[PDB]
Protein backbone atom coordinates (compact mmCIF):
# COMPACT_ATOMS: atom_id res chain seq x y z
CA UNK A 1 0.00 0.00 0.00
CA UNK A 2 2.93 2.52 -0.50
CA UNK A 3 4.25 2.10 -4.21
CA UNK A 4 5.70 5.56 -5.18
CA UNK A 5 7.87 7.46 -2.67
CA UNK A 6 9.61 10.86 -2.65
CA UNK A 7 13.30 11.72 -3.12
CA UNK A 8 14.99 14.39 -0.99
CA UNK A 9 12.39 16.66 0.62
CA UNK A 10 9.80 15.66 -2.04
CA UNK A 11 9.85 19.00 -3.84
CA UNK A 12 9.83 17.08 -7.19
CA UNK A 13 7.03 14.75 -6.04
CA UNK A 14 3.97 14.72 -8.13
CA UNK A 15 2.17 11.55 -7.07
CA UNK A 16 -1.31 11.10 -5.86
CA UNK A 17 -1.00 10.61 -2.17
CA UNK A 18 -3.71 12.65 -0.43
CA UNK A 19 -3.53 11.55 3.24
CA UNK A 20 -1.61 13.13 6.10
CA UNK A 21 0.22 11.55 8.97
CA UNK A 22 -2.87 11.59 11.12
CA UNK A 23 -4.90 9.78 8.43
CA UNK A 24 -6.82 12.93 7.50
CA UNK A 25 -7.43 13.67 3.88
CA UNK A 26 -5.97 16.68 2.18
CA UNK A 27 -7.99 19.67 1.16
CA UNK A 28 -7.92 20.45 -2.53
CA UNK A 29 -5.34 23.15 -3.44
CA UNK A 30 -8.28 24.93 -5.13
CA UNK A 31 -10.53 24.94 -2.06
CA UNK A 32 -12.37 28.22 -1.24
CA UNK A 33 -11.48 27.68 2.39
CA UNK A 34 -7.84 28.56 1.45
CA UNK A 35 -8.48 32.10 0.21
CA UNK A 36 -5.76 34.21 1.91
CA UNK A 37 -3.16 31.43 1.84
CA UNK A 38 0.00 31.52 -0.35
CA UNK A 39 0.15 27.84 -1.33
CA UNK A 40 -3.01 27.31 -3.20
CA UNK A 41 -3.86 26.73 -6.91
CA UNK A 42 -4.27 30.49 -7.55
CA UNK A 43 -0.60 30.94 -6.73
CA UNK A 44 1.16 32.41 -9.88
CA UNK A 45 3.47 29.38 -9.91
CA UNK A 46 0.79 26.72 -9.14
CA UNK A 47 1.70 25.23 -12.55
CA UNK A 48 5.37 24.73 -11.67
CA UNK A 49 4.67 23.74 -8.05
CA UNK A 50 2.03 21.15 -8.95
CA UNK A 51 -0.71 22.86 -6.99
CA UNK A 52 -3.85 22.41 -9.11
CA UNK A 53 -7.42 21.12 -9.08
CA UNK A 54 -6.57 18.20 -6.89
CA UNK A 55 -5.73 17.32 -3.23
CA UNK A 56 -2.45 15.57 -3.68
CA UNK A 57 0.54 16.09 -1.41
CA UNK A 58 3.06 18.63 -2.49
CA UNK A 59 6.00 20.43 -1.10
CA UNK A 60 5.91 23.83 -2.90
CA UNK A 61 7.69 25.83 -0.17
CA UNK A 62 10.81 23.86 0.67
CA UNK A 63 9.51 22.10 3.70
CA UNK A 64 10.77 18.69 5.06
CA UNK A 65 8.59 16.33 3.03
CA UNK A 66 5.25 16.69 1.12
CA UNK A 67 2.37 18.28 2.94
CA UNK A 68 -1.17 19.62 2.29
CA UNK A 69 -3.79 21.76 3.95
CA UNK A 70 -6.30 19.90 6.14
CA UNK A 71 -9.08 20.52 8.49
CA UNK A 72 -8.57 19.20 12.00
CA UNK A 73 -11.97 19.49 13.63
CA UNK A 74 -13.31 22.33 11.37
CA UNK A 75 -10.08 24.24 11.89
CA UNK A 76 -7.83 25.05 8.96
CA UNK A 77 -4.31 23.89 9.53
CA UNK A 78 -1.77 21.94 7.40
CA UNK A 79 0.15 18.66 7.93
CA UNK A 80 2.83 16.44 6.50
CA UNK A 81 1.76 13.72 4.34
CA UNK A 82 2.06 10.07 4.69
CA UNK A 83 4.36 9.48 1.64
CA UNK A 84 7.29 7.00 2.29
CA UNK A 85 10.73 8.51 1.63
CA UNK A 86 12.50 6.58 -1.20
CA UNK A 87 15.22 6.13 1.43
CA UNK A 88 12.46 4.59 3.55
CL1 LIG B 1 0.18 28.60 2.51
Image (cartoon, helix red, strand yellow):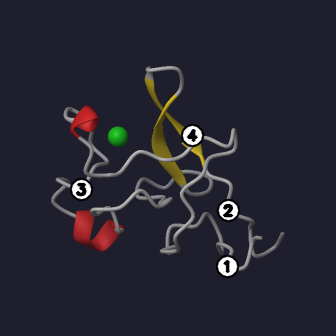
Contact (CB < 8 A) between labels 1 and 3? no
Residue shown at the point (50%, 67%) measured from the top left: 11
- Identify the element where label 1 is drawn: loop
Mark 2 / mark 1, whichever is N-terminal: 1
The outermost residue toward the right is 88
Numbered circles on residues, count: 4
Identify the disc placed on residue 79.
4
- Mark 3 or mark 2: name the one nearer the start of the chain: 3
Where on the picture, by quarter, is residue 31? top left
Cα separation, mark 1 vs mark 3, equals 23 Å
On the image, numbered disc 1 is attached to which residue? 4
Left or right for 57, reference 6: left
On screen, residue 84 above or below 21:
below
Disc 2: which residue: 83
Q: Kindly state the secondary structure of the residue where label 3 is placed.
A: loop
Element type at mark 2 = loop
Are the two marked residues, 4 and 1, in contact with CB atoms closer than 8 angstroms? no
The residue at which mark 3 appears reads as 41
Instruction: Determine the residue positioned at 41% across, 45% down.
Output: 27
| Mark 2, other Cα within 10 Å: few <14 / some 14–19 / many ≥20 | many
Amino acid sequence: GNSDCYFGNGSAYRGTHSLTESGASCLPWNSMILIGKVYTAQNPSAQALGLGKHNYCRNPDGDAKPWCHVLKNRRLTWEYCDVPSCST
